[PDB]
Image (cartoon, rainbow, N blue to C red):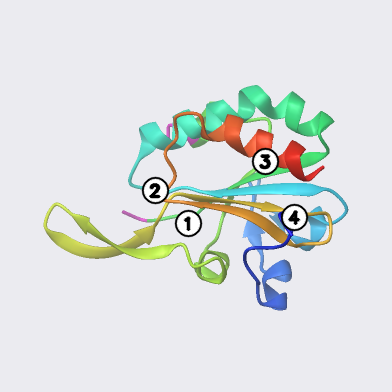
Amino acid sequence: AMTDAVLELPAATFDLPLSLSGGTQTTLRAHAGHWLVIYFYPKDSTPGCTTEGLDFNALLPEFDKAGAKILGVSRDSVKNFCAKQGFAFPLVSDGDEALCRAFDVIKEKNMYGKQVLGIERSTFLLSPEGQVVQAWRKVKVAGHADAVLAALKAHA
């Protein structure tokens, strides 16, 4: 079926702690009951974080009416302008990369000659019950938020 899930997640993924602004935590289980757009972004790209975030933020009202919430995910790294933007949806930190690994977004990247591990910009659409109905990996930001919104309505 064109509505079937494209990825299967370990059950424990739904209770992994994600750190919010203010310091409290949230989980995927807390988002059960409504559609959820979960997008992952790399920390090494502030401009990309800012633009992808503002795009989803501008469309938040339509996502809300379509029955979905949005969660932006990354991993706090010792090595901020995006976080200061003030998106109307939560940005969370996956401290030990547990959630990232569950979605398999940690990939080998070339950073100025040195091979490192990092987050491959990716997005996932989950149903009210947790089914991952659609995925986007190594995302092209141009038109992405619009495409995710379209996908949400197509599954509605």
Upstream in sequence: badge 3 or badge 2: 2
Give the magenta part as a residue range. 78-82
Residue type, label 2: Lys
Upstream in sequence: badge 2 or badge 4: 4
Upstream in sequence: badge 1 or badge 2: 2
Disc 4 from disc 1: Cα separation: 31 Å
Q: Residue tagged by mark 2?
A: 43
Residue found 63% across the figure and 22% down from its top: 58
Tag 3, which secondary structure?
Answer: helix
Q: For residue 28: magenta?
A: no
Asked if residue 81 is positioned above or below residue 130 in the image, the reply reads above
Upstream in sequence: badge 4 or badge 3: 4
Disc 1 from disc 2: Cα separation: 7 Å
Upstream in sequence: badge 3 or badge 1: 1
Upstream in sequence: badge 4 or badge 1: 4
Disc 3 from disc 2: Cα separation: 26 Å
Task: Say whether marks 1 and 2 touch (CB < 8 Å).
Answer: yes
Quadrant of residue 17 in the image?
A: bottom right
Residue found 45% across the figure and 37% down from its top: 49
Asked if residue 23 is positioned above or below residue 132 in the image, the reply reads above
Q: Residue tagged by mark 3?
A: 151
Say which of 89 and 105 sits in front: 105
Q: Main secondary structure of the magenta part?
A: loop
Residue 27 at least partly seen: no
Outermost residue, right direction? Answer: 33
Q: Residue tagged by mark 1?
A: 75
